[PDB]
Structures are given as structure tokens and as C-alpha cells.
Image 1: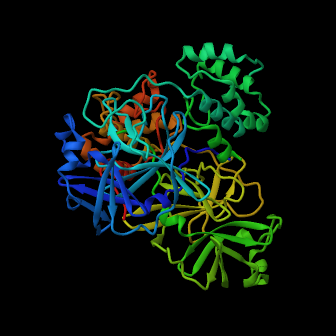
Image 2: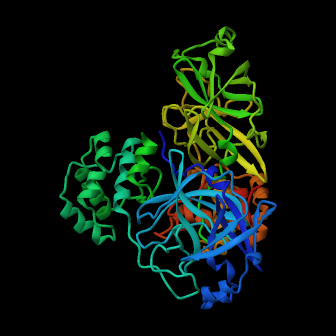
Length: 301
Length: 306
């Protein structure tokens, strides 16, 4: 019983974190086998970032200008190359703490854990979701760049995010582990801005099933609705439209609570139009959307 | 930027989690050097927890009856004893992943990270607080017993909680690592229930200071209050009485922001009596109470771990 914003255990990732320094700029790198991955803008100064040319900058660097450090110990860089917005550094020794891993690109609406680091040292872990506009609402002070986001399935770490930038509104932007940005952002100081965000409807519905599972059910009602009718209301409140695929995905939770998906949709429709009237659900006075259906099933069953 | 509730990196604790089994009863244990700690009620298999004389069952149990598992490896139990509500198992191997650690008993209101575990394997990590009524609002399923709560200071792991049980309201009760329960609770089948709880005033104030530190300061006003007048109001909203000791604890955040504690109390008084008017504080619609003053300093000034 109970329900918490829960992160994956971060141990397997902790053992891969390192420090990468170029002149006066230091950030975090990810050390897997004999390769260290970090954001390429490690080779920039605060002034280089106005309009950097990374090809220009990188050619003026040698293996020797990169200072990589695992805790106290320096690692010898014997190769370097760029892969999109990532720098790859080869080191002359392999990380024995390297876990079973893959690099995955996630979709908006999906969640993952972040291991915030500074100077190659793990500081904290938290769970978040990839907003529909491709930003993350993160907790990232300066020097956190290079920190990674991940999921764990069985004994395998799926890396899905590396932190690169903070945007004018205070939200965060980054890449997958191939250096490709989520969203239309770039690694330079531009007036770039995130699109208007939306509420992840599928996740809200999952969260309401979690509430019902934990005994919170005042918001339920006798009505049912059609998908079309629900979408017309949801979209008026800046909620993502719901699809049949998304209804199908809520199936197990529906079965577990014996509340039909379209009945739960009718409940949400009423909450949207009426408000909560000070009341709370699972302790919150607003509808939460950073839990996926699988997250709910995992925690509640 | 951005502000979020964060757990400590759990790696150093993951390396200490094992599986402890007696008969059909399996739960989690904490493996430090050559000792494994787990809830004593693991010997109840699948025995009614009505009125068991743990002493007796324990005197009857053999070393070979405990199945301890660390990964694919079965640890050989070579000794066993009881320490209050905990079982201590001596094994033939000192845990190679033992970090620097200490056992501490925490105060109500204090926060910690919990590594939820099942069958000895870590499944998830979250941050929570010891409620004033001596329970935690955790997230636990069956088989989570033995999961631990902890803080990390530099390179030292301070273990402060081991999970024992769930109460009728869905909240949770457990012990420190000496095996002494938080609250009046016991590890047997009884009519025990959580008492009425309160909002951790010290933490809300710390959180308001965090907001200001982060440039979120709309709720500040130009008035002040006495401690007594603050308590008269706040206690009507089910807040814990604030003491002079709490006021002093907030001192460093008061100094950093230049806002006297009683001045911040007046803003909170105004927030309680008037609501927020749909506005947010640190992106939150409710007054957060699971961040301590030290949590705020740590996250805003610094801070990493070895």
C-alpha cells in the first residue's frame, strides 16, 4: 500500500560516472567499457556558446587536452571523436563496473530515473517524465551536464537521456546516448524555447487507477462516456487526446479494479469540468501525470 | 535550476541487500561485514504472529535453517542472536561491498531515503519523512520487510530505518538498526493503530526558504509575528507547534536569505488563512513538509557524495 514517485536503484549507473575537464570547463561523463561519453560542449567556454562551431573547436584539441578522472584517478585518453552532440573519448582501461546496458530512445510521456551528478560525483536520484514538448522538469544546477537518465529492466540498464542544456523558462533539454536531441533544441545559447506543454492523459488515468487501488475513490461516478466525447473535453483543457491503443493499455488496471476505462474517463471528464474543490487524491490537489501505466502496475502489484 | 524531492544515490546500500528465508517466509536482510540484519519475525513461518515468544522459536532454530542469499551465492550462516526486534546472523564471509557506515536513531520530522526491496533485490528508491506520529507514508508491497532507510554524509552511510509492518491505514512502522521500534508499535498481531498525525512545521518553513532561495518569493509580506501567535493559528490547521529550538535550527537559512524566522512565520500564517489563490510555490499547489532545513542547505548549497 502507499504510492510514491519512485526512482530505479541508481547503483549500476553510479559506477559509470566520471569527471571530464577541458581547460576551465568541467562536467560529467559516462564510462562504459573503454569509452567515455559526455556532452560535446565541454570544449566550449561560456562565451563559445553564443555561436559555437564544434568541428572547428574539436580539431584544435588533442587526446591530451582532455582530463578524465574516475574519483581521484586520471584516465589516459587515447582517442576522441564526435557523435552528433556527444563527444566520445577512448581511454586505455576498461570500467569493471560496467553493467549490462543498451542505449534507447524513449517517447514523450514515458518516464525514467535521473542520477544528478556534479564533478563526476553522484548527488541525488529522482524520477521524471519526458514532457510532450520534449523537455524535462528537472533539478539541475550548473555542472550537472553529462548526468544521465535511465530505466532498469531485470539486470539491464537502458540509458535514454543525457543532460545538455537549461532553457529560458527553466526547463531542461538533452539527448539520447547517440547525441541526438529530444525536440528541436540545439547546444548553443539561442533564444530557442519549448512549445506549450500538455498534460499526459494516459498517465493521469493510470494515476487515478493507483488512487482507486489505494482506496481513494470519491471522484468516481455512475456515468460512462465515449472516446470521442472524452477527447472533446480533454482537449479543451490542454490534455492529450486518448486513443484506442491507450485504452487497450489501461486494460490490466481496469481488470484489477473492475472499473471500465471509459468509466474512469467519465470520472476524469467531471474532474476537469468541475475541479477538485480543495479535495485531494493520493495527497495531491492536482492531477499527476508523471506515472505511466506500467509504473502504476509495477508499484501497486 | 528546478527543485525536486531527491533520494540519495542508493548504490552503497544496494551492495548490502540480501535475501533471508526461514521455511515459507522470505524477506530482506542488511549485510554489513560478517553480520546480516533482518526483522526477527522472519522466523515466523508461516506462523501466526499472534503472541509468539520469539526467544523460544529462536532458541529452537538452527543455523542451517536460515537460507541467506546474496545474488547467486548462498551465504553460510554460522551464528544467530536477537537484538530487540531484529535478528542478527553471523555469516562466514565479510561483505566485500561494505561501505563506511553508522547506525543512527532519527527524530520525528527527519527525512531519509528508502530502498524498497523484494527477495533481496532492490526494486526502487524514494525519499520520505518520519511522521510526527512515528509512522512513514511509504510504498511497500508484501515481502518488503527488511527494506532499509538511510542518509549519506560524505562517504558514510547512516542507516536509520528497517521496515517491519503496515498499519490499518496503509502507513508503515519499523525500527532503527538496534531493533527498537519508532513509536509504540510492536511486531505482533494486535489492534495497534497510527495516532493522529500533524504537519511538520519546521519542514514547511524550510521549504518556504528553499522557494525564496530559488527566486519564488511572492508570498513574503512586511509583517512579523510572535511565536505564540503563530502557534495559535497554525495548530488550528493541524500543524506541529513550533518551538524556539526549531527557530534556531532554521538559523542558517534565515541568515542566507536575510529573512527572520518569525517574519517567515507571518507569511506562512497568511498562506494558511487565505490559501494561495491558485498560485504555486516551487511549482507546488500544496505546502511541502518532507524537506528538512538540512535537505535545503544540501540541495541548494552543493552537494555531492564520495
